[PDB]
Amino acid sequence: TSIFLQEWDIPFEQLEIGELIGKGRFGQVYHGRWGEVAIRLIDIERDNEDQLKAFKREVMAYRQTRHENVVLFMGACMSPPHLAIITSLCKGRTLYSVVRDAKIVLDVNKTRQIAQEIVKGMGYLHAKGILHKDLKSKNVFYDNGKVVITDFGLFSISGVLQREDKLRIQNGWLCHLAPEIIRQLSPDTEEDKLPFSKHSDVFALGTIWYELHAREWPFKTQPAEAIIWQMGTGMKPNLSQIGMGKEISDILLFCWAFEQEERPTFTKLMDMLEKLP
Amino acid sequence: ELDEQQRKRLEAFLTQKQKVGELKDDDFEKISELVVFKVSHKPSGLVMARKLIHLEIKPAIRNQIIRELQVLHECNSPYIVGFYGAFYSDGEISICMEHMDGGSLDQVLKKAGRIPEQILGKVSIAVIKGLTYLREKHKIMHRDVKPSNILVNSRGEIKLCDFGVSGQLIDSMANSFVGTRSYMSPERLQGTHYSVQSDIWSMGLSLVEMAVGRYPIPPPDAKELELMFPMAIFELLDYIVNEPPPKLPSAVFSLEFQDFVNKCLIKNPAERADLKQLMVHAFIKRSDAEEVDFAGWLCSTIGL
Ligand SMILES: CNS(=O)(=O)Nc1cccc(-n2c(=O)n(C3CC3)c(=O)c3c(Nc4ccc(I)cc4F)n(C)c(=O)c(C)c32)c1
Ligand SMILES: Nc1ncnc2c1ncn2[C@@H]1O[C@H](COP(=O)(O)OP(=O)(O)NP(=O)(O)O)[C@@H](O)[C@H]1O
Ligand SMILES: Nc1ncnc2c1ncn2[C@@H]1O[C@H](COP(=O)(O)OP(=O)(O)NP(=O)(O)O)[C@@H](O)[C@H]1O
Ligand SMILES: [Mg+2]
Ligand SMILES: [Mg+2]
Image 1: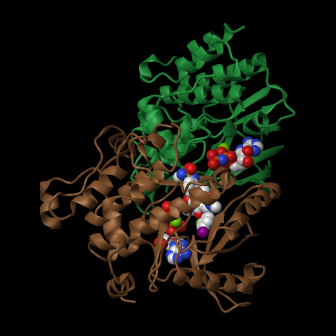
Image 2 (image 1 turned 180 degrees about the vertical axis):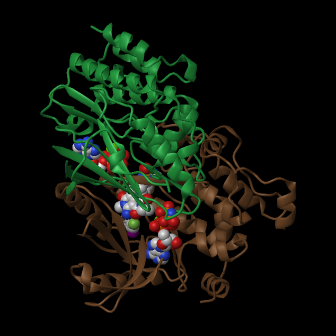
């Protein structure tokens, strides 16, 4: 029923909380000091024992992770109703901001390299049986060639969907969702019971690959209902309109495959990415 | 496309909008919730409706938003809700407009059982002439006609609202809501080129929903149509795209009305009736030359 901060292998004496780093839908993220750290404060119901034990299950999972392309989970302290997760702080900017910066050049070699970094991180997480469930460019950080994945697993416990008989959909979300998931969204849908899988993570990486080359999300023009229908029936863009070769488009054809079993693992994807010009 | 009494009311609204000059937060005192609020301007004795769209982006884009929104000062019609001004306050852009004491046809249909055919005829004329006005004098399509955006008053006017004037406001909104009732045309769902035909489809679907008292997709079985007189978003959308369109029950509605909606609900937008074809359709020629006290039915049903 309790998670203390002395339960962790990172020795902890004091924790300072600084300014808010940015807005977001799941808790608040502050600057902190331990070196500098990122502290995500989350609120839960006073006595929802169910989800609390689910949460501890998950963060006990996170305590075993360490990998250069994965944000360092440093500790988590629970004490209801308010819980906090403390991770390492990422220098640099999100991939989201970098992609949308006109002064930044994104040649095909550099995009292939960024993709390979993200793929290594994701394959590490998969090998430990951890699904991300919210892979996207706002959850990847880029600092002069160093690429780090953050916020893995949170989506299960997130509550970012929460009007009456109306599901709240954030821009950018739907185009990362594999068809199997898109075809199940409802106003009754709950984050903890959507059919996430390794294949849906590979799908989201495919969406990231598109965004890396077009420098915008797919389906940018279209409203949400159109996106749901088009993706659920399997219509997907390509990159020929901007002169990308066949090889850069085959990554999309594979990662976005309609039937899950046709999508590659991150190991196979790493191989496919190595063989680009 | 001209009347006198309407001219008078529009002149009066122009006179009124002269009163306000400029707007800012403290001018307004919250009266009630309608997000949209019924509010009282203090610099001028007006009761307005103020809708607050929460946007969180840098000032240059919001300035572009207000520049684009200023076009509504220019559009004026008896079939368009009145616009007064748009300012920015505290991470929310405000649109203040004429307040409609009858509300949207969504909630009037919610309180009534079903809306009778002749009133639906009147509202059909209102909507078709409003859309024709927008297309012909401002080269804009509404892009979001549905019951909640059609407004009614105790004086008896029916006008369109919440139509698509600003592309940048479409871009700037962070997140949308998708429920169990879609009014998007099949061609828009599929991402092909579209025109005001999509608005005509949305109007048809709204009309059949209001006439039957139930959102008509999926169509009800014999049991619920008898008594009248758990679905995932994707399969509703796929029904709209691939199943034959809804249709009125053949017993309780006129041939003209049935054919009017059927012409609105044709899937191929090229074969779907256009604005003027509907302007000359039998159903609205019949409804045009009728005397219905819309204000009376309204007030009696809503208790106003
Ligand atoms: C889902 N289809 S979509 O993805 O393509 N997006 C989209 C499409 C069509 C319309 C809008 N839309 C809109 O829904 N509302 C309502 C918030 C719920 C708008 O108020 C709105 C708008 N304000 C506005 C203008 C005049 C009056 I008189 C009153 C108003 F409230 N203005 C200026 C717009 O230009 C658009 C384009 C609006 C969004
Ligand atoms: N380790 C970190 N280092 C630096 N910034 C971080 C870190 N973790 C989170 N942030 C920032 O904190 C803010 C909130 O992030 P978050 O709560 O995850 O929402 P988001 O993923 O950015 N957007 P959304 O998916 O709609 O919730 C963003 O500006 C992030 O860039
Ligand atoms: N000028 C107005 N006069 C009267 N009621 C209004 C006015 N503007 C908005 N409303 C009401 O405010 C409520 C909220 O409408 P709105 O913000 O448009 O969301 P919605 O109706 O639930 N769905 P949508 O219309 O598609 O955004 C509805 O009940 C409208 O009828
Ligand atoms: Mg994040
Ligand atoms: Mg509305």
